Image (cartoon, rainbow, N blue to C red):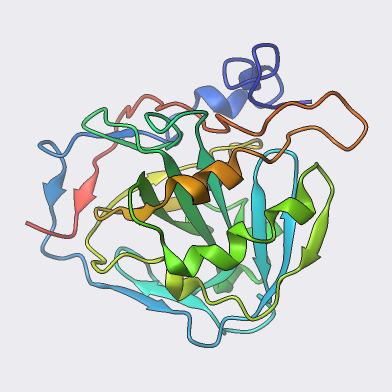
Length: 257
Ligand SMILES: [Zn+2]
């Protein structure tokens, strides 16, 4: 029953998911002046050359592109991480207008959207077990600003008309997620949570400093999706972001000076 509306949105989630008021919730505001450069942090290793995308799905909260995670084909390592994390899916959060949509913020600045590339720690064997562990998941977060088009996003944009409503999916093979990355892998990192129910406190967040640019036409296509199922009153899938949560006793570390 949870969603992003007045009666089921983020301010309501704690009733079914009390960890919503926990000690390591996401997203957060990244205060750039307070984040500590950590020279012990390693470069991130993003190994997506053998990625195998499977499907694209409207799940009623976002759209997601799903990958074969049954072998080490597209993996995240290094950075703040110990061990190997397999790419399972990516999805986005976005706004009704360009001045909101991101989940993380940077010195209170909201971006138009935020891409989450979701990975799970192979030492737990499957994602269901990983979400029960404090180091179970690593989510790579990438901000989107509106300007020039992102060519590597266009294949995604062009199939969204086929998954307009909740429950629709389509074949989405041979998609290369490397086409969604910025030039720099400079990042901030902190321990946090899933940003949607069940809000499990299982995520090492890795948020890239450099946004990607997408065009107004690309983000407009996101905003034509629907939260509702076919047949139900049409409610545009916009503003599917959770606001910044209290940092509490956490330190955000920077990979860069
Ligand atoms: Zn997300």
